[PDB]
Length: 100
Length: 79
Image (cartoon, rainbow over all chains, first blue to last red; front, side, top):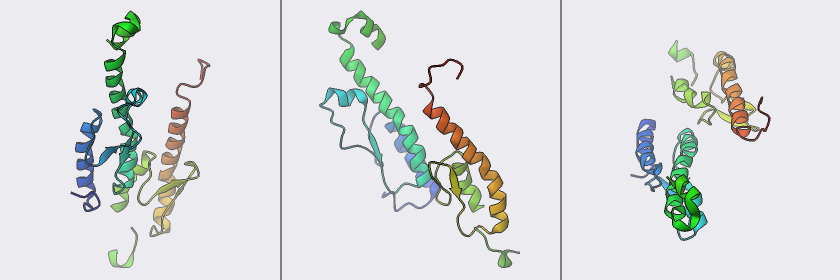
C-alpha cells in the first residue's frame, strides 16, 4: 500500500516498525530505501555503510524518530562488510583478533 | 460547554513527540531549537498553560544538543 494513502497514525507506526526491523540489519524495506550514492562495488562505500532515504509521505515526527534510528543499520552493515575484508592473513594478528 | 468553547485530547496525541525534542505537526521548533511556536486554534488559557509545560521540552532539547555535541570532543577529564 502507498504510504500517503494511509492516514491513521497507528497503522503508519506499525508499518514503519515492521520495515525498520529489517533496516536495522542493513536490508532495504518498502519505505526505507538505499541512497543512490551507495555503490556496493567501492570498498570505502561498503565499509562506511549505506545511507538511507525515508519516504516523503511519512509523518514528520515518525520521520524524525526514524532518521535517528536508521544510523544503527548503517553501523551494522559497515561492520559486517568490515569483517569480510580485513579478516585475512595480510592484515596481521592484531587486526584479525579485532575482527573477532 | 462544548458548543460555546472552541479549541483544538488532540494536543495529548502530539505532545509526547514535542516533549522529546522532536518536530510535531502542530508544534514546530525554529532558530536552532531556541523557540517553539504555539499554533493558532489554541485559545488564551491553553496557550498560557502550555507555555509552562513547554519549558521542559526546550530545556531538554538544549541539553540533548549539548550532550550530542560535546560527547567525545572535550579533552579535559572534569568536563
